[PDB]
Image (cartoon, rainbow, N blue to C red; front, side):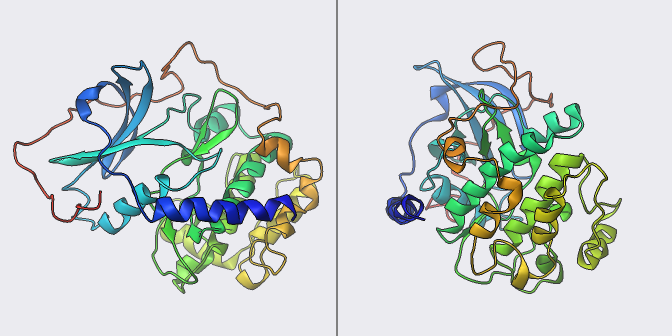
Length: 339
């Protein structure tokens, strides 16, 4: 709490500015060669693109102006830009450019090849307590950083946790994020990581985040996640009851952390407590972990992926290809003047 407070404040400012002044138009579609579709969205597509000049692949999220309105996702779609545009941190995915064209919007991040976590996890089976720790140590620092900027994250999961050439992580998709102060009431995110506040809908807060950190971990360490059924409503009652079963192989300090996070009471849940993050940051489980090396990305990674070369999409899925349409007249240029 010496060096780890000069930052946060130093870091809260840097951000503020950007926050409060976002470059917009920074490129045009043509500067890029569309290579391949990476991930999806009900309001866009994330695909692989090669920058003409600098043979640098990036990754282009492209939301269609007309699909984001039917879901008013505007309010949102605008801060994801404003955030990535101001947010700044190692474990955060870099935004390089943002432009819009007649029809749909574009955010162009750095390309994290290694592939999304959710998959290695399913491939491998589960993670070894350390392995999981390696990651967690990265979320904790991450949410420490964020939370300090009045930014709940709202959408933590393995599909958002991408893996770089050095097994470290970068979280993508700030599409649910929200700079706030106090309570907010939006029901957003996968039913599986839903803190039980959200479920009743009684204005949650950053606390819902730390809760997802547990679900994160549990699952990282078990494969399966704590709460899970077939159909959503079911998973719902499950969560509120809060009866969690630990697999036999859980370390003891694993099972400790957990039930502190997976705490159906905010007013008694690490992350929400008066000692703040230091409750977690100090939990035995993190005994060995050196909070700087990680940070400083000086630590040697447990895992890795093999990249055949620059812009290798092996670690990724195969989706159906589509075009990048651009009707002839500025469709929906009203609501997106900020973009």
